[PDB]
Image (tube, rainbow over all chains, first blue to last red; front, side, top):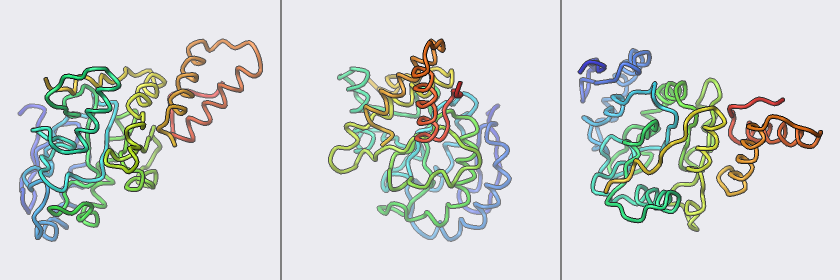
Amino acid sequence: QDPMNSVTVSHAPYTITYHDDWEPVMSQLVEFYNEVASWLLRDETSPIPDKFFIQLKQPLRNKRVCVCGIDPYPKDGTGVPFESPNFTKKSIKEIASSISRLTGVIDYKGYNLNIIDGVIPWNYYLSCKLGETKSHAIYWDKISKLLLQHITKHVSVLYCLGKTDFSNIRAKLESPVTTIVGYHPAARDRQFEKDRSFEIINVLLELDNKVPINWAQGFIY
Amino acid sequence: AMTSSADLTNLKELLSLYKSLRFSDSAAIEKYNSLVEWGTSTYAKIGVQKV
């Protein structure tokens, strides 16, 4: 209500609510979202339009990692990337699994990247058409670029899951940032089982005289 | 690869050398500068300079 702000757009969800940190992008966000929202609102979406932008209420100034997926869960997206509030989606169960092995906690009820101090979970594209992944890529394009640029002004490390999804991510950025492109948790041959991005990020941060990430905080007991 | 045990193992060694930062042969410094160059290339940017 006090760090929070509001701007009004001409298409569902009409009001975008953001944390102060996002201010320099909003003018353009508004403008772009107005040009495309008609077309993209034709389809039913994951998440619902009222959730598209709920991740703009997260502060950026305290953020050192961004853990990025290409788009939301083709079903049941909550508007908070990776979040499965009943701990059912595979990708988040497989991530919880990597971090059980790493930090050695084997008793947990759920896991959420969005509570972990200094991390912002993100979706490159902010909706997909229900059941279909990457369905709204063409709609989100210019916006996705603009938001991710901004995020990388504040984070030390960008961590993108999806080798093929994010093969050419470097192209999307102005100035360079520590970028790591790992495997998707649903990748073939258990390749994410042996992917060690969570440990790698920490070393990278130490090299930037930033404090490591406490991956265990994300557990729900 | 950027995501493997070897990648992690190289980055720790680089961290180790950076803390010391106090070399005593040509191979030590050229390993470090070589690790830094590799880090930069594999991950685009890291938080330490070549010495």
